[PDB]
Amino acid sequence: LMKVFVTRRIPAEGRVALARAADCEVEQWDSDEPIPAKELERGVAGAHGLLCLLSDHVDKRILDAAGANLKVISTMSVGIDHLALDEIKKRGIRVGYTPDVLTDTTAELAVSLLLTTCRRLPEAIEEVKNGGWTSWKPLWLCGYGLTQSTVGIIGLGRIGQAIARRLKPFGVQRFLYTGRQPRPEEAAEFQAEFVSTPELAAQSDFIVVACSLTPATEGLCNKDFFQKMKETAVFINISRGDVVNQDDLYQALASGKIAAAGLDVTSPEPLPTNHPLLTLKNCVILPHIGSATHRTRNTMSLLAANNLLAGLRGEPMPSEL
Amino acid sequence: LMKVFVTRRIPAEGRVALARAADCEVEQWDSDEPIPAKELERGVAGAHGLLCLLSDHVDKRILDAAGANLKVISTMSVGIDHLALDEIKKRGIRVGYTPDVLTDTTAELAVSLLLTTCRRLPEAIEEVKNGGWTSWKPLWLCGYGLTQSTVGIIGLGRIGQAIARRLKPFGVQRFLYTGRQPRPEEAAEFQAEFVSTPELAAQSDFIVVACSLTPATEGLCNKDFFQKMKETAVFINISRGDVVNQDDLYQALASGKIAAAGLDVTSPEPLPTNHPLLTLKNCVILPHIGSATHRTRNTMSLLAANNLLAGLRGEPMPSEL
């Protein structure tokens, strides 16, 4: 029997699929809490397969603890920045990941974050709870909406495209995107215009970041970037925390260089409860719930399970990296 | 000089317009707080024109205090259930209202409220602030989304259509609506299907109430309605508080007859802070911010101002009821 380590309690369908594989011995971290480095090193020892999560840093150390038996890592995420890919490819280890199945949900969460930020729901909710609400008021809790807006998207991949698609009927006048390369075919549906980062910041009323975390994008959204934004604009990040310079953001939000921000990702995760960004009424922070619907999480789980199983058996994977 | 009473501080552009009318004497309630009944009676005495708000109950008593000078009431709202329409038409008084200008913002707000509610943003926000957040967790904060959902809309007028149009690209498979009368032409953009209230509640994953408050709609969303809803379904109201039976809604939410609710309107307004509904983690309440963007509020103000002046001068009004 081949050994499999799962780093967390996962959605049922995925766990059952693993429990059904007669050729597998499945060891599991029986918790909702992230597995410490030390217990993961202990757990992957001798494993033929690792099923892991975003949260788990699979670097050279883990690979070494594994070590030689490891033929397949299967991550329950589309993002891969948590894997030491170069060491993995050197070792001839196969990788499963979960693109496509979370596209709609993540785009959906991204628009929810956009709207609750720019329409100021969190302040509004609190005004109800705290006795601030006394009547309907013509001047009160006004934000900025999407009618005739310009929306700037950083990274026009499947998720960005699906954000643009949900945004269009709110009356968006023009879509801009940036990246390393124009994508006419993907942009055509929205008449998106490929522009530089400086131009994107200058022209947009809304900025949505939906790219991978890479050397080219680390610290991309910094002081120079917020400076170029309109003071009436709203900044949304659903990529990785390290794409944003958090101190520059705070400062931009505190001095009014931009109107508001909504973050689904931060650095680190979790964010400390005493963090400056959390003292700000125009910053909305979500705890990385992009893909959080029942249906989506269940599908991701079954896909991770199936990637792992095909990996173990030397077969084509439903979705391999 | 004709006398004009304004019942609150309104957006600048509207007050500037009034302030430029050399044919007018403009008295204003100098406050963001709602005008008491006694102060309103006092202020309308001798008025030729009344510029009022949704919050203001313009009933027989007010008109009497006015009394005989009053020729024009201008409301900065699309809703009119706060006016004694039959008394007004008997007295030959003209009415201005603000349709159309707030259609896109309101629809925009209703979609924000739907997304914040079904994607559990408020719970999510508090878990970051209260230390609940410890990692990325596969089973945590999962809501229900719109992919292949059925959306049911009560009242498919301009705002309902504009909700439908925003929701379509989130992957809605089926729109249903109810009302007093089918609307083929207005429904055809969405292939929406006219259905009875019981069928609406039975079939929908999301229910959005966007109708006027009338005798036929008071207490419409009650115990039998919530019973017929899917227990996975989400209920949104942007119409008027009195369309819902708040106690039935509370009970439905507490027992799990439905998955969650999001209300932009309540009974009364404001809702008391110790209200049962506000002890529920699966009820989102906003303080009636449907039309709260700077652009829209300013447009509404100018419209209400211009309706008033045209009224005073016996001319066609930009938007008359």
Image (spheres, coloured by chain):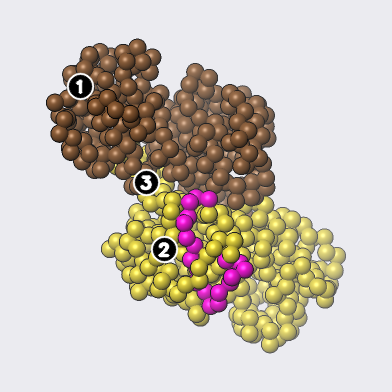
Chain colours: A brown, B yellow
Query: In the rendering, at what x and y percent does residue B90 appear?
Result: 68, 87
Q: Position of residue B204 (x, y in %)?
A: 41, 63
Pointer 3 and pointer 2: residues touching (CB < 8 Å)?
no
Residue sitting at 65 percent across and 31 percent down? Answer: A194
On screen, B158 above or below A77? below
Query: Which mark, residue A47?
Result: 1
- Residue hosting label 2: B204
Q: Earlier in the sequence, mark 3 or mark 1?
A: 1
- Determine the image quadrant of residue B191: bottom right
Q: Residue A161's spot in the image, x, y percent?
A: 54, 39
Check the image and name the residue furthest to the bottom: B90
Dot 2 alpha-carbon crowd within 10 angstroms: few under 14, some 14 to 19, many 20 or more: many
Task: Place residue A230 in its image quadrant.
Answer: top right
Q: Contact, CB < 8 Å: mark 1 with mark 2?
A: no
Could you tell me which secondary element the residue under label 1 belongs to? loop
Mark 1 chain: A
Q: Above or below — where is B293 with respect to B20?
A: above
Q: Give the amino acid type for the residue marked by disc 3 in the picture.
A: Thr
Residue A189 image offset from top left, x and y in percent: 61, 42
Please tell me whether mark 1 or mark 2 is closer to you in this view.
1
Inspect the magenta stretch and tell me whether residue B182 lies in it. Answer: yes
Quadrant location of the N terminus of chain A in the rendered image = top left
Mark 3 secondary-structure assignment? loop
Task: State whether residue B288 appears in this view.
Answer: yes
Q: Amino acid at mark 1?
A: Ala
Residue annotated with mark 3 = A293
The residue sitting at 44% across, 73% down in the picture is B197
Q: Which residues are magenta?
A: B169-187
> Number of numbered discs present?
3
Question: What residue sits 35% from the left and 73% below the top?
Answer: B223
